Amino acid sequence: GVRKGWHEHVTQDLRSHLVHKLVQAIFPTPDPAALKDRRMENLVAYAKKVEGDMYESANSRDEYYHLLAEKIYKIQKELEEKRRSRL
Amino acid sequence: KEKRIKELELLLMSTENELKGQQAL
Amino acid sequence: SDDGNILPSDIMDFVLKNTPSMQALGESPES
């Protein structure tokens, strides 16, 4: 028996845009040229690996989103006060 | 900190509504 | 419960370098 029965609700468009939106909060970049630089490919590959691990860690689409958004919350709001507190 | 927290939490979970909606239910 | 990492060192260093902010000066007490 396996509780996972939610993969059929997902789309390739959702997968693509959620990987993209993961990257936007993992590192917002200094300027839009920094999204195109070769070092951002490491950030992008890390975001792809995280997306797949959070997907595999979930028995529902809601739990998958919750796991994505909690790790996004950590990565964004930890650095926003450890490195950007003065805003 | 609250507006940007709800903003971050919503920013991901809105994507399925942006791409394929919820009017089917 | 646990407190394990989520941000590998190679990717961490790239986000750590870019996200800070700084200031500068060059005054003197001389007259």
Image (spheres, rainbow, N blue to C red):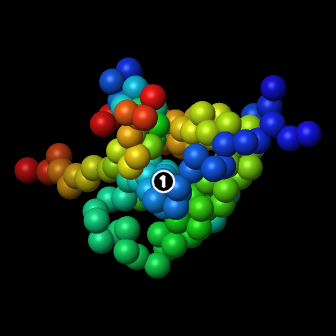
Q: Nearer the viewer, residue A40 or C30?
A: A40
Q: In the rendered image, which quarter is residue A57 located in?
A: top right
**Lateral position of residue C7 relative to residue A21, left or right:** right
The residue shown at (63%, 50%) is A8
Q: Nearer the viewer, residue A58 or A2?
A: A2
- Quadrant of the drawing holding the N terminus of chain A: top right
Q: Furthest residue to the front?
A: B24
**Lateral position of residue C15 relative to residue C29, left or right:** right
Q: Considering only vertical position in the picture, is B24 above or below B2?
A: below
Q: Nearer the viewer, residue A7 or A25?
A: A7
Amino acid at dot 1: Leu
Q: Furthest residue to the bottom?
A: A38
Q: Is residue B11 visible?
A: no
Residue position for label 1: A14
Chain containing the residue with disc 1: A
Q: Considering only vertical position in the picture, is A49 above or below B22?
A: below
The secondary element bearing badge 1 is classed as helix
List x then y, in percent, for residue A24: 41, 53
Q: Furthest residue to the top?
A: B2
List x then y, in percent, for residue A84: 39, 40
The residue shown at (43%, 35%) is B24
